[PDB]
Length: 49
Length: 49
Length: 49
Image 1: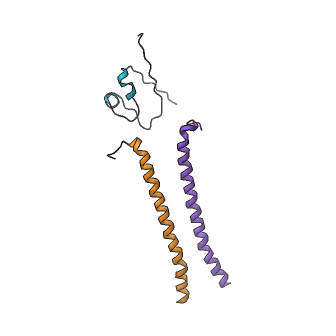
Image 2 (image 1 turned 90 degrees about the vertical axis):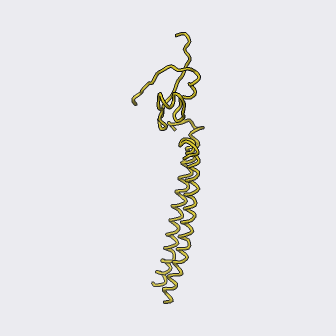
Image 3 (image 1 turned 30 degrees about the horizontal axis):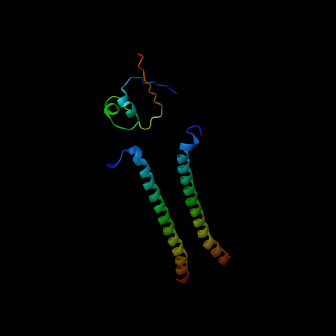
């Protein structure tokens, strides 16, 4: 129910940090992943564009 | 609280809950065991009196 | 079943088993506690009759 897609582009140095419950430069002050949240995260490199 | 974040400390909290609940069930069992022991004794004392 | 694959859901199944087995042991203990309470009462009623 109610599929929401949050899309952005980041450097590979912070890709491993985005996860629901940790800290960091981006995880603390740019977005908040809830701890009880259930979902999926997909990251893929895009050099051609 | 000051030793881990809620996610990973949750498993230690679970062990704390389990051990203490089982300590309570042993204690309550023994309390009612001695209560039942005193039950027959109290009926015995009522019969004597 | 529809919520995780068997490997990682196994740990939640273990908690489900543990809580329910302990609920049974408490319930069975209390049942026999009241059975023993009724034991002396029934011998008492047999003595009266």
